[PDB]
Image 1 (cartoon, rainbow, N blue to C red):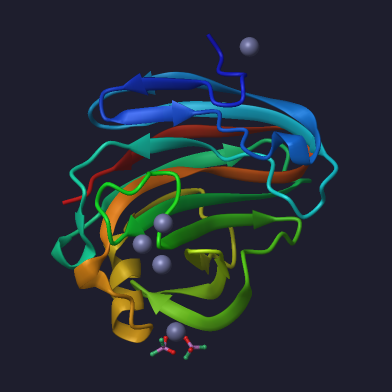
Image 2 (cartoon, helix red, strand yellow):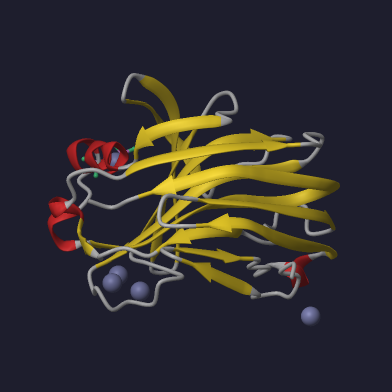
Length: 219
Ligand SMILES: C[As](C)(=O)[O-]
Ligand SMILES: C[As](C)(=O)[O-]
Ligand SMILES: [Zn+2]
Ligand SMILES: [Zn+2]
Ligand SMILES: [Zn+2]
Ligand SMILES: [Zn+2]
Ligand SMILES: [Zn+2]
C-alpha cells in the first residue's frame, strides 16, 4: 500500500517511513509515499506530490527516520549516513533535507526539540530556511550556508548546500561538532532524539522524490 493519509506510516527494521503531511491544511494538493524496501542496512522509498497555496508554508515532510539509541551529543562518536536521491521535476519550490532534533530531556517528544538541526542537500525555487543566514560554514571541506531561526522553544540551525547533493555521504556529527565549537551548542546536555531524511514541499508538481537509498547510524 502507498502511504497517502496525513500520518500514514510504515516500519521496517530500524527505518520508519512517514507521509507526514503536517502542513496539508496550509494549501491544496495531495501526496503519497511509497516504500520500496527497508532493512537493517538502509531504506528506499519515493514520494509524489502536487501542492499549491500557502506559498511560504511547508506542506509536508515525508521522510525516513532512524531508530537508534538516544544519547547526549557529546557522547556521539559518528553519525555516518548516505543519501542517494533525485527529483523528476525540479521546477518546484521544495527542499531535500535531513532533520534532527535534540532536547535536554531524553524523553522529549520526538517531533520537536530544544534544537533542530537541518542539513539541506538541495533547495529548489529559492525557498529559504527558518530565520536568516548567519554564516558560511566549512564542514568536512565543503561550504554550507548556515541559517538560524527560532519558533517558540525550538531553535533551528540549517546548513544549506549551494548545489544539489544527490549522492551524499557524510558524518552528520561533523555538523554537531561545528555548532559545539563555533556556536556554543550545549552538546553535553542535549540528547539526540530524532534523525530523519526527506523533502519539504512548498509549491509545485506533480513531482516525485525517489530515494534509492538512505542509510544512517548513530554511534
Ligand atoms: C556570532 As552569532 C551571529 O552566531 O551570535
Ligand atoms: C559564540 As555564538 C553563541 O554568538 O555562536
Ligand atoms: Zn486514507
Ligand atoms: Zn520542548
Ligand atoms: Zn527543553
Ligand atoms: Zn527551552
Ligand atoms: Zn552563533
